[PDB]
Length: 163
Ligand SMILES: [Cl-]
Ligand SMILES: [Cl-]
Ligand SMILES: [Cl-]
Image (tube, rainbow, N blue to C red):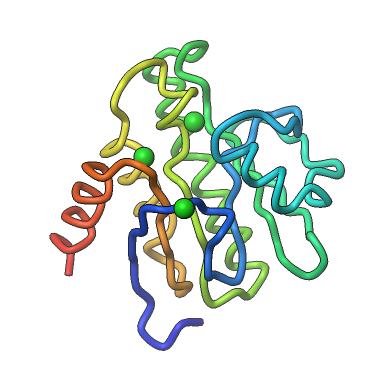
């Protein structure tokens, strides 16, 4: 565990993280994909051996000894708001189980279903709150990765409001 488990946010490519493991915003078929998934494929391609897993689940594959946790958020183009919300909460619960099983002291995590899978909605708060629900009972240092300057501000404010 971390000595004083924390949440932080950084605005940069998750493929350059300084944590003991990474969460990929995966597709269910283990394909290279686009966005976070493509950056993860270029950095850790060995981790996409048998990485396919259903929506709402997480599957870990090692790249050397570095764990890549493939977490499959729902595509809100295809799911109802209700079913999508349930699957997005479930993907994060499975990430917390994997982070715990691996025994890491830190994890780099993107906001699931906030990009191409958002169904053209702003899901910062919805996705971040499901991340907190899952990860609050873990003792890993969590570092959230984003790319947008105003998202960095909003994520940082949400973290600091609980401290
Ligand atoms: Cl960067
Ligand atoms: Cl996404
Ligand atoms: Cl972002």
